[PDB]
């Protein structure tokens, strides 16, 4: 398809296929109407993604991953193009995806029952399981890169890090430890917690501060865990005041949950239990995504009866 | 632009050094570059500059370049010069060297010196590898 036009969106120029109509802003991403599919879509511009060695490797991975992965809780790729005609001309990539109605930041902020929180978390966990099954650990799961539809369907937008908002990263990442799949479970816990509490669990402007909120709430890790850290990280961490932390009953009381819910005392204890197994500093004692999906709080949703030449190269497929 | 930490000592990122204008306004005479990749600004005499060739990682050792680093800052204040300590972002590597410098000259501990720099440049967040090393440096002093 070679039919291109241009529109000024805010400070940028989008130059897209004629099929994408009436662009409105929401990378820089605008919304459009796809005349050939008769639905709204999102168009994300990647400008000079090879502006350097880094943008290249992140863009190429995302671009490859987006093309070969597909699952219901991962945002769907509809199209990929470049308005430029040559490899020399080559400047910008456009990614067309399906368009949701809101990001998880907004949704967190709404008034949610147990049924909806459970469903969002369940979807999150399936998205992640699918990623791990493909050998992809996300390591950067945040409410801002998760979007949800009006009817509560949840899609994960990105594939995470290779290989500023730091609030959802696992202790392993701050502590320089090795990580495994259940790293992503820590992020889920943070999100879950945020949904119940009504605000970020561990809000901080740097590593020190992050760690602090973490230990102030969950308690200083035991000596066995301290010994797992490399010498230097260990000397810094063992030098920080000790904290007893709080039990999950005190961190997540009943009152925080929506008030007139059928069976909420049981539902709140299920939620607290799940949290208590997710917000666990020692990753070797933290639950897995598979165990999480089987947890009483989440398992209601299981149904037994159902189922730069490179970049440019990759854009022209 | 870059953050004044002390009189004659600035802490910044590579976009700061590469900006001729900003650099001319502050008086940036010297450069302590704390990265392997960030190049010297076309306008700084070699002798007025220093690379501390380190990466921002958990395995990098920035402790053995400390002494060198503080001297270079001290030396440049002796000639009555103004030093910019930077790395790619001025968040981790360069902030670590600035803090070491604060610890030494103000007889401050890591906690105190970190807070001193942090109040002036709130985006600083050196990794725990570097902070552990700074505790080790606290001892030497
Ligand atoms: Cl940095």
Image (cartoon, coloured by chain):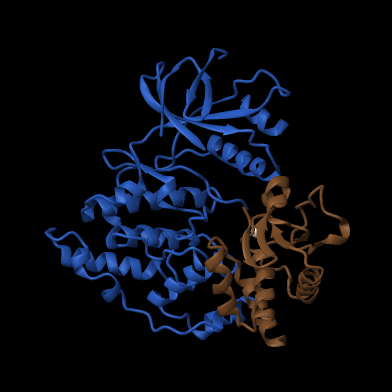
Task: For ligand 1, give the image quadrant.
Answer: bottom right
**Residue drawn 18% across the image and 67% down it:** A255
Residue A307, can we see it?
Answer: no
Q: Is residue A178 above or below residue A115?
A: below
Q: Is residue A10 above or below residue B94?
A: above
x, y percent for residue A10 = 47, 29
Quarter location, residue B66: bottom right
Judge by depth and name the residue closer to the eye, B111 or A191: B111
**Residue drawn 52% across the image and 85% down it:** A223
Image mark count: 0
Judge by depth and name the residue closer to the eye, A90 or A127: A90
Quarter location, residue A275: bottom left
Judge by depth and name the residue closer to the eye, B29 or B121: B29
**Residue drawn 51% across the image and 68% down it:** A171
Quarter occupied by the N terminus of chain A: top right
Identify by letter the chain in blue: A
x, y percent for residue A146 = 41, 46
Q: Is residue A224 above or below residue A131?
A: below
x, y percent for residue B44 = 82, 53
Q: Is residue A272 left or right of residue A308?
A: left
Q: Is residue B87 left or right of residue A237?
A: right
Q: Residue furthest top?
A: A3
Residue A78, can we see it?
Answer: yes
x, y percent for residue B4 = 62, 63
Quarter location, residue A260: bottom left
Q: Is residue B35 left or right of residue A303?
A: right
Quarter occupied by the C terminus of chain A: top right
Q: Is residue A246 above or below residue A89?
A: below
The colour with which the image depicts chain B is brown
């Amino acid at each position: 398809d070679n039919n291109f036009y241009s529109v000024e969106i805010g400070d940028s120029t989008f130059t897209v296929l004629k099929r994408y109509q009436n662009l409105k802003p929401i990378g820089i991403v605008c919304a459009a109407y796809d005349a050939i599919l008769e639905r709204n879509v999102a168009i994300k511009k990647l400008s000079r993604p090879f502006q350097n060695q880094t943008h290249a490797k992140r863009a190429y991975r995302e671009l490859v991953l987006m093309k070969c992965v597909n699952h219901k809780n991962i945002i769907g790729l509809l199209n990929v193009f470049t308005p430029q005609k040559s490899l020399e001309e080559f400047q910008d990539v456009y990614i067309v995806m399906e368009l949701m109605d809101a990001n998880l930041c907004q949704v967190i902020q709404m008034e949610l029952d147990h049924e909806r929180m459970s469903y969002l978390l369940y979807q999150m966990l399936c998205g992640i399981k699918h990623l791990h099954s493909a050998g992809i650990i996300h390591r950067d799961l945040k409410p801002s890169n998760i979007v949800v539809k009006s009817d509560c369907t949840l899609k994960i937008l990105d594939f995470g890090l290779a290989r500023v908002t730091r609030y959802y990263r696992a202790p392993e990442v701050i502590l320089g430890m090795g990580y495994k799949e259940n790293v992503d479970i820590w992020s889920v816990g943070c999100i879950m917690g945020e949904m119940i509490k009504g605000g970020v669990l561990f809000p901080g402007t740097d590593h020190i501060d992050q760690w602090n909120k973490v230990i102030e709430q969950l308690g200083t890790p035991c000596p066995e865990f301290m010994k797992k850290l490399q010498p230097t990280v260990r000397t810094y961490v063992e030098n920080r005041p000790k904290y007893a932390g709080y039990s999950f009953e005190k961190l997540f009381p009943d009152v925080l949950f929506p008030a007139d819910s059928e069976h909420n005392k049981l539902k709140a204890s299920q939620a607290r239990d799940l949290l208590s197994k997710m917000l666990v500093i020692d990753a070797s004692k933290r639950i897995s995504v598979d165990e999480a999906l089987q947890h009483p709080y989440i398992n209601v949703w299981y149904d037994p009866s159902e189922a730069k030449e490179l970049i440019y190269k990759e854009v022209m497929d | 632009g870059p953050t004044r930490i002390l009189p004659n000592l600035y802490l910044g990122c590579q976009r700061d050094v590469l900006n001729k204008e900003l650099m001319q306004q502050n008086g940036i005479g010297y450069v302590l570059n704390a990265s392997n990749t960030c190049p010297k600004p076309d306008f700084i005499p070699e002798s007025h500059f220093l690379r501390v060739p380190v990466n921002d990682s958990f395995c990098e050792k920035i402790l053995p370049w400390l002494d060198k680093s503080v001297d270079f800052i001290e030396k440049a204040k002796a000639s009555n010069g103004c030093v910019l300590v930077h790395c790619l972002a001025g968040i981790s590597r360069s902030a670590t060297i600035a803090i070491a410098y604060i610890m030494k000259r103000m007889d401050m501990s890591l906690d105190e010196a970190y807070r001193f720099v942090k109040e002036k440049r709130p985006t600083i967040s050196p990794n725990f590898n570097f902070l552990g090393q700074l505790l080790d440096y606290e001892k030497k002093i």
